[PDB]
Length: 164
Image 1 (cartoon, one colour):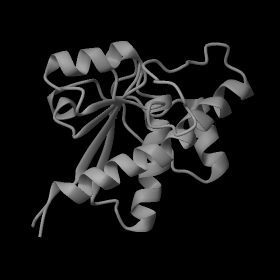
Image 2: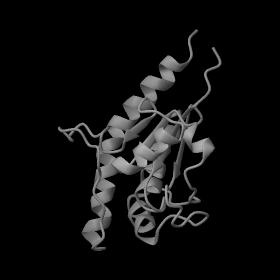
Image 3: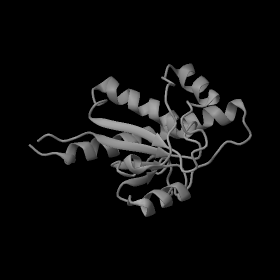
Image 4: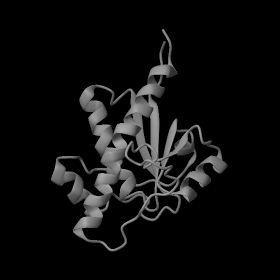
């Protein structure tokens, strides 16, 4: 069975902060374990803030501080993104837009909603407007906490995707 790779596209306002953060985080882990080609992780922003830009200076420092890659080119929520197998929304609105645009809740999932320590349903994720050292590492924690949930999802889905 020639099962094509997964497609996790994270949707946040800007696509230069939280989205690219998890992008390099668990996706790097994927290829590090041998699943980098088995799952296509991507990202997009509903408001195309820094579309065409690169990862935000704050997140770049965060990732690089922990040894994570930081290269990425921001994209807007488009067709190819809506075609993803998993749209990791960072907020109730982003998720809503994607699904109404052509996606569905089967594909669209909240980033913190993968977090095993979440407890309650996460239909909305925080956002650090204060802009301190805490704000940056905080988001990193959000994502790293979801990676054990995002992993399982992409893994389980990519597994069942193709048969023998």
